[PDB]
Amino acid sequence: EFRMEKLNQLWEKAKRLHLSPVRLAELHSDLKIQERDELNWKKLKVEGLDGDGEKEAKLVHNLNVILARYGLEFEEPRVIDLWDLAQSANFTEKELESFREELKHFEAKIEKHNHYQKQLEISHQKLKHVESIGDPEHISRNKEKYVLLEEKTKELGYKVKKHLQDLSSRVSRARHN
Amino acid sequence: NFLLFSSKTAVRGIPFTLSTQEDVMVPVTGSPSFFVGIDFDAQHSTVFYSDLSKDIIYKQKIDGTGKEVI
Amino acid sequence: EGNQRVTLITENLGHPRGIALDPTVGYLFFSDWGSLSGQPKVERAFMDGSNRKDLVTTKVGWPAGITLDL
Image (tube, rainbow over all chains, first blue to last red; front, side):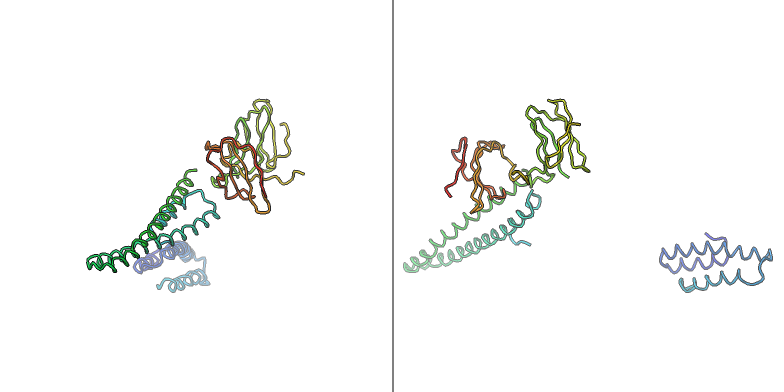
């Protein structure tokens, strides 16, 4: 890389120190520039074309400083699916925002439906215990609850299914057009 | 930008987006007309077309005015 | 006096024939004796063309005219 004797010695240290490669690359650059200046300076020493010490000072100044610089949002699977598909539909931003609010209301509906199905299950557990007990008054009361709670739960079931069909069909239509 | 297309009935311009389907330029139409060729000059906001039924080449602005024979 | 042209409805329009509106409520009604989809219908929109609905669809046939009892 360098003709110069003592610049070859200095250049090895920077490899050993693993300095910043860009600064390391620039360190080669100015040393390759300096070696031309250094040989030029000495070329005057055999040519006797300097006696004022300029061509020594100018080069050692840079070298000495070089010694310093280098040391040298949804919850239900169905609404998530509908939102994911509706993202790729031909919806206007206004229709997209209205559709977002519609999925929020649909999500509230499905949460209500699953809450009442779980209530229909714990009322079924109470009904199983009562039927095993066999008390006619307990059976009559638990029926008055259960047989009407079933219809309330099922009416929500129909309404959630219809809303899901409408939303899914509208998204599928808005994906092809 | 919009999608310029030509047919026998008319020359029309529709948005590239499939949501907002309404035309964005006045549909060019003639009585015996049969349109084939189209191009545009967006600096003057004009469209060139050829009525193959008349054998005439026209130019017309986007807003529907300024029909002239080329 | 025929200024400020702008198109409201164009999608699916088939054969639009009848039209009526009630600016006091903001609905626009128009009839259509066969769409690009095939179905003839009477439909309702807002007066800006948005939020279209099949207002009548069964046994519609060839709806030719519309008026409103305001």
